[PDB]
Amino acid sequence: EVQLQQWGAGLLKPSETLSLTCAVYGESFSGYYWSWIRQSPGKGLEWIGQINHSGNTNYNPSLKSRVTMSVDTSKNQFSLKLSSVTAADTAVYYCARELGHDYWGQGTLVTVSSASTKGPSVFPLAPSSKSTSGGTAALGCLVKDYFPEPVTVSWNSGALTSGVHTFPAVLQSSGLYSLSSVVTVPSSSLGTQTYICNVNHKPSNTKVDKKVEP
Amino acid sequence: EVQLQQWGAGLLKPSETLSLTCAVYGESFSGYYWSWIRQSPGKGLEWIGQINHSGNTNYNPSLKSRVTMSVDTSKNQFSLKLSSVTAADTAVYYCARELGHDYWGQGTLVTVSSASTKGPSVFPLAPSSKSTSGGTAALGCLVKDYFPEPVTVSWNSGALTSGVHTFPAVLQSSGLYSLSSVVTVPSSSLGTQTYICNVNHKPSNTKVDKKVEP
Amino acid sequence: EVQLQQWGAGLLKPSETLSLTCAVYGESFSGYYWSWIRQSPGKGLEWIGQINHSGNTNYNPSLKSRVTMSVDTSKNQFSLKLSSVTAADTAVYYCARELGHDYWGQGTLVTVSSASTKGPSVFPLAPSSKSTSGGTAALGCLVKDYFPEPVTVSWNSGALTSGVHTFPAVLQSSGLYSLSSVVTVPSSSLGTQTYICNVNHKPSNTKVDKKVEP
Amino acid sequence: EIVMTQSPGTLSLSPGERATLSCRASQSISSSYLAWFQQKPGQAPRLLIYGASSRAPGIPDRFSGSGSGTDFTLTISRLEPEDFAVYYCQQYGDSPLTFGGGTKVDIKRTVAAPSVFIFPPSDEQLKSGTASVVCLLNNFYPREAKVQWKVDNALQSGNSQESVTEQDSKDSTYSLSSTLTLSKADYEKHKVYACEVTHQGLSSPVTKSFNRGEC
Amino acid sequence: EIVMTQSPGTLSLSPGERATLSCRASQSISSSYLAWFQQKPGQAPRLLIYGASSRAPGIPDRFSGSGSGTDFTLTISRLEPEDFAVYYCQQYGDSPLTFGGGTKVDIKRTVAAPSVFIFPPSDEQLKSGTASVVCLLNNFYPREAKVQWKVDNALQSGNSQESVTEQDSKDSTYSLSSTLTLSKADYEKHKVYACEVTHQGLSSPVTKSFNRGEC
Amino acid sequence: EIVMTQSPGTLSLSPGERATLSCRASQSISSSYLAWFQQKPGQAPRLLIYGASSRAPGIPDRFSGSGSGTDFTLTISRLEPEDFAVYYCQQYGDSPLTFGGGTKVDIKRTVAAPSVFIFPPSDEQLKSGTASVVCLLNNFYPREAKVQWKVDNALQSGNSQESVTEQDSKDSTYSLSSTLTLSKADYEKHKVYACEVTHQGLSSPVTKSFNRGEC
């Protein structure tokens, strides 16, 4: 019952070299082949290669000129070095056994992009007359132009949870993501209560408390 | 017309590399020169350099060996890289047109100092018998030893608005800042109403509601 | 009276390199030896090495093949480079004079562990009838898994601060810390007033408030 | 390089029915070496069937594999609630381990109707340099939906993008939001804006329009 | 590298009064290519005069430039309230662009009297390990205030820092506070603490002091 | 590499009482080059004695040192409140600087009694797959406190870890919590859970067990 653990650099820039390491615990490490499996959105699971304790390596013919692997028998570690990463190598990388039939890793999301850290610029989303459909409305606060992926959006400091729909971030053609968060409330609630969305973004330490004004 | 948006690393440490980016909107990007202008306290406006869509660059002879500029025509963005920043690079950086005759950016306050993030230590400023001139007094709460620039001082959750005087932050010879905030109130009202100065510091995530004791 | 301010990466992963830098302010920087001293839990203070303005280095025989200091006379700074850090390098690093007699640094905690950031999980702990010896019992919620060290557990948002004991974090074999906090309150007060163990994991931005009652 | 192809990825079945999955391969897989993986969201894949007929140890009996040659099938007799994930088929009879495209199963419910709402760009966003117009669809089960933007009574293609949320954990319904990223000059040079939405829950498509300049 | 020099930056003029500024360059500006910039607090600079004689489009005719060769001047006919900012002059007829030192104009009013107050250090600061003595001035118009700390009837220089408040938006006065930080040994070895406040609004300089030991 | 050793692991003396320390070295120091450091929690170490006999500048005369050869003693005449920290000793007469193992001093008071509290595993964490059993002690002065976990009237060791809190600043006592980890089937089939406590507060050890299935 091995417990594979992974680590490596998440953010990367184009034309650099990806480097990941997977540590093996539990039972014996020698006399086995250790695989690297890459899963990307749009595509499916992809097999990268294998390596054993003796340094013998098997490579996927497609990713053969850019893949280099090394094994460290001293500390029970094997590593992957994908060279000249482009924007198409943004995926989730796994480490498993030779066939990935018994035990897998945990996954290490690796994103390749050329952009500096930016703070989100939240904008209000006014509920128009058409939004006020008698007993239902549609609020929100569009969150735009932040580079690092993880952004968490709340409402009324977590007081409001029903109807909240935080849509997935979308990478536009500027290197920066965009996110939306909305909630539906009755019109009387609009006229009798104030709503603020507490967008926060750790890599820039910028948290905003924009209030939606009807 | 054009609209320029700026983003970059604000807080820095000595011997690092400053990296700022500016984005061009509204009108065409190709066919002009884009400038970086620095405004340091004490000194005046300084012109750092220029770059166009073909990578042609002009540099100020003062900041010649440390300034490196790159352009990205695809995303309509240009960037500045100031290498080996010292404590003299604390200033406000602008991105503008050819010579800044038409349109400027907004400004990115960049500070270079070797000091860890610290939280404010607010102390009561008791009204001395000399300061209590019968009908005129002066309260306040000194704030000391906080490294990051931003800090806000309130009074009774914003109830006190008239008579407040928030002095500018002063950097002593220790790499940290010290700020004083005072308010003037009648001596008789001192014992009747409780005056609490709500000082907070965003980088350290603190909210102190210390009471001033005579 | 010199001021020794230092900065460096406070978190690391195995098989990586450790970089620290200390800055000297005030008196002269040349004509002296600058030392790096490590204080590890369990063990005692350990002397790593020395360096002067000319690059002459003294080394600890134990940490001889992995330690390398460099000096920057231009900006009055010296640095430490520890290569291939393992789990045994988790300690606090100081920069001082040659013998550490006059002036020391501030203390830069460095932790080496191969674990990704994970959100804490709160497990309520009901007070047993055996625990309730008439009016004396103990409440609490056991936080099980969280990678980064900083975490705070408070009761009633600071309303209940009497009788609260916060035990130190325990590093589990998986690489995830564990914390337990309990409160001693009368049974009548427990029945009349509900208690919540608020948590605020800064790295994961998780604010989970769980109330547990008999 | 045996290219594995699967059934459509949007297979929908209510809990309590039989699920059929196909992994038509490119060539004859040697010795019927085909494995069926399952990947719950946020986790790593797990084996269910090895050898195209035998279940892995610790796997319940609801998963039954079959097939031989270039046509294989995985059958789930009773779709339990914790079985709606993405299933991949892996062939290990050839040197490069090739995984299938993967198909996912989701809960089936009665058809609903989207709650369409549109919004105008904010003043601060407008002065920032760009104008974003977004119209939203709320609580519709059939994931298939088309949003067609109309600017000055003209069709706009490629100048927009949309995102969808995952299946709801309470009523098992989706939500769609489509944004119309437009420049300041282009936004201010047009009169009317609307997005057309087509769904099988509404026989007549509904178009919600707003005019810039009044609220 | 044409070094630019300007008139003293403390030009104080009453509202509705003609204002003049100087931009004496170090050499002869080519083709009178000299521009004047105005920067209100918190914003980027904007043009007023380009070519040292012609006003930029979108600026009221109250701003008039003059001069040629080496010495240049800027003239304001009427000092509107929205004109109290810092004015920079820039030349664009050489290889590196150079801006001036910048001169600011503020509201001129009647002289006021500095309300002086003194605050002794608190006990928690003393137990922390440092002692800071602050004496404050309230509602004094002129910028100049030579507040010198007198301790033990001796001369102390350099061991103090001061803060100056910006223009007041209601009555246009200042507020200056200076802090006298000292070590615990120096704090407890000295007997009298005072700051010598001097002002042109008071003919005879005055001083307020406190002594440690009484309250 | 002169290995440096300190004999008293944890000295505990009442305030205002003389304290003596030992820094037995492994070799003979060159010229009595041995120093004594003091490290208040959360701060950097600070010198008190240099040369094994002389006081550092600014150090109160309450600190005195002596000894030569391979035995060195540090004597504190009066234990002031700002004296309870860890004390390290350092040598110079060899190429690598070597620090002592470190010894700490704390305030002494009467012996208290541990209040044993026992808690069962929660249902949520049992579902998660971890069966954690914890027993706590509250407000006991002596540092020594042993937790002997017994499972089904048997002896088990090495499956538990102990956490100790820093001394309370009001009553000057300690609280100890020990966590016992268990598996799924092991917790399911085992019946009786208890931890045994040995302390000098009570001559007769006290045990308080529980049973799973009733409360």
Image (cartoon, coloured by chain):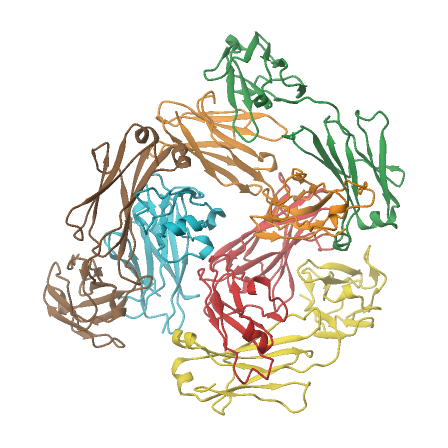
Chain colours: A cyan, B orange, C red, D brown, E green, F yellow
Q: Is residue D197 above or below residue C123?
A: above
Q: Nearer the viewer, residue D156 or E80?
A: E80
Q: Is residue D136 left or right of residue F212?
A: left
Q: Is residue F193 left or right of residue D138?
A: right
Q: Nearer the viewer, residue F27 or F151?
A: F151
Total label count? 0
Q: Is residue C170 left or right of residue F99?
A: left
Q: Position of residue C161 (x, y in %)?
A: 62, 66
> Quadrant of the image for the N terminus of chain E?
top right
Q: Nearer the viewer, residue A132 or A51?
A: A132
Q: Position of residue D148 (x, y in %)?
A: 21, 41
Note whether residue F89 is visible.
Answer: yes
Q: Position of residue C160 (x, y in %)?
A: 60, 67
**Picture quarter containing residue F7?**
bottom right
Question: Which residue is drawn at the image coordinates 18% and 75% (left, top)?
Answer: D54
Q: Nearer the viewer, residue C110 or F167?
A: F167
**Picture quarter containing residue C39?**
bottom right
Question: Which residue is drawn at the image coordinates 32% and 45% (left, top)?
Answer: A131
Q: Position of residue F201 (x, y in %)?
A: 68, 85
Q: Is residue B208 left or right of residue E211?
A: left
Q: Is residue F98 above or below residue D116?
A: below
Note whether residue A84 is visible.
Answer: no
